[PDB]
Image (cartoon, rainbow, N blue to C red):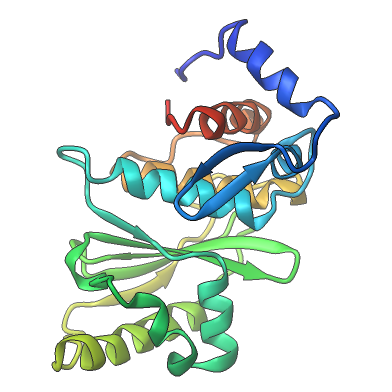
Length: 225
């Protein structure tokens, strides 16, 4: 059971996959821009680009904040890769005006080569979790995030981070797995959608053509269905 894309909605979708002004701004929000060219990476089995992922992640963050949902901060795609390669100093900056400790969930999209995955800090559950639709385990990435939270706590609030009961880990194939390499960004987005709603991750690989069509639609209306 999944909201339907009416006729109607497909017409809006088909229309934007058409050839035309590549610079045409289809959606503008969150400091970001979605063009015709960004939207096209959602087409067929194209690899998503960062603008789509970031834009989507910001929609989840915007949706958090409505009543009853856990509150969410989404880090932008470059954050982790700038953190892994350069350390805390190079990213400490990125969280001015943001108290990363006042939300329930932190979303961290992880770019490893051609591949996408996701880490999630859930402060309610006191744990840090890695999701890969290929089934890769990434121990390291969780530790790197823990270590970042530490240095952020010392820096933003003058206190050490309290690791008691905190659990760092990767989901094995307890999550639906990809078949199409190019769907990795879509699994990362959809993992985050369920998680930020506290809903079980119920879909599989077969829903991916539908999810691509839907995200085009959602992005264009800035409405999550």
